[PDB]
Amino acid sequence: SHEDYLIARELIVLSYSNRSTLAKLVSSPMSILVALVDINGTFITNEELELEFSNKYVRAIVPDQTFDELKQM
Amino acid sequence: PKESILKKLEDIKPEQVKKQTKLFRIFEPRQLPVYRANGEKE
């Protein structure tokens, strides 16, 4: 898709230049971006390991020092 | 889409409290010329 083409155009050209920093700069904010999405209906596993389904709604609460650590990423 | 009818319920904020910043006005005093009983200006 066209969402794949803009990534493969900016990684094929760049991986000819920097072999070191490129794999970690793109893969950096995914440790931060996992904390922004809300929970609508989630899976769960109870204590003896078996799968249930839960429906709880939990907000995502991030401070302003995450959106200042994401702008520097 | 049971996650969409739940999200409408968490999105209902309490009622928007309104405070006004100017007095409610319909009428203003305007400058109109005045004439005496004969007809000419006063």
Image (tube, rainbow, N blue to C red):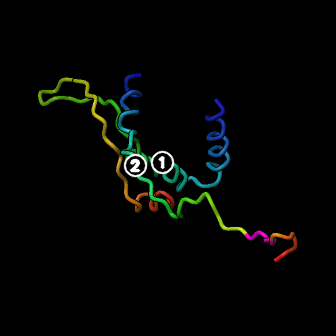
Q: Going 55% across and 52% down the picture, which residue do you hit?
A: A22
x then y, percent, for residue B20: 48, 60
In this rendering, the answer to whether B20 lies above or below A59 is below
Q: Secondary structure at mark 2?
A: helix
Most extreme residue toward the bottom is: B42
Specify whether A65 is left or right of A49: right
What's the amino acid at mark 2? Ser
For numbered disc 1, what is the local secondary structure? loop
Q: Residues within 10 Å of mark 2 (few under 14, many from 20)?
A: few
The answer for how far apart the CA atoms under marks 2 and 1 are is: 8 Å
Q: Nearer the viewer, residue A38 or B18?
A: B18
Q: Chain of mark 2?
A: A
Q: Residue at x 65, y 40 (%)?
A: A6
Tell me the crowding category of disc 1: few under 14, some 14 to 19, or many 20 or more residues within 10 angstroms, Cα based.
few
Q: Considering the whole magenta stretch, tell me its main secondary structure.
A: loop
Residue matched to label 1:
A27
**Above or below: residue B38 compared with residue A34:** below
Query: What is the span of residues highlighted in magenta in the rendered image?
Result: B31-36
Residue at numbered disc 2: A31
Question: B9 left or right of B19?
Answer: left
